[PDB]
Figure 1 (cartoon, helix red, strand yellow):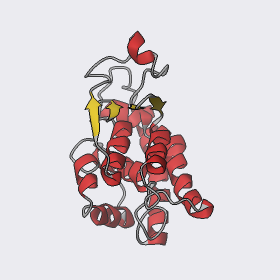
Figure 2 (cartoon, rainbow, N blue to C red):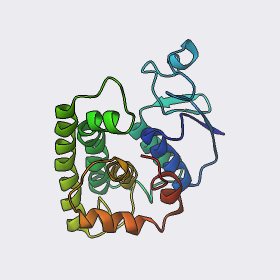
Figure 3 (cartoon, rainbow, N blue to C red):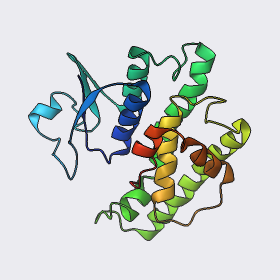
Figure 4 (cartoon, rainbow, N blue to C red):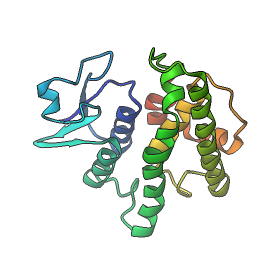
Length: 207
């Protein structure tokens, strides 16, 4: 049985949990992470030298890095419907998956740590606002893409890219900041409410 190592509140663990549910996988999840079970111990570092979650163990195969994990699971467990093999279709998915991790996630760092995790080390009002502003610019890109598709982030069909992207949008919506009206974004999140796993792991009250 697939093992998922990571606390269920982590956005990156939720990418993995959502993907498992969508694909139809059985799994066991162990709590690891800040506030649950500390990862900076030898037994965990041996699995992931980053000491971060998620990590999966699939038989003797150990993998870390959430976007890499969800790609693996879709590739391994009959997920061609979710992550299409055709190069151009897959590229449309990858662009948003990769951008989510490299630009969107980066943008929200200070504001999220300050306002949601209330970190004692992130109390600079100027940097909170700077992060919110930058985050908002990235959310406007998400909005334009969804106006263009009128459906899902990569096109007409729910895909792997919607998992990182919707979870990111959920984080934006659950952070106590003033936000511009983004109607394509709102219509997308309403569209996703039909998916059981979105309700369970994405729009479930947790930032």
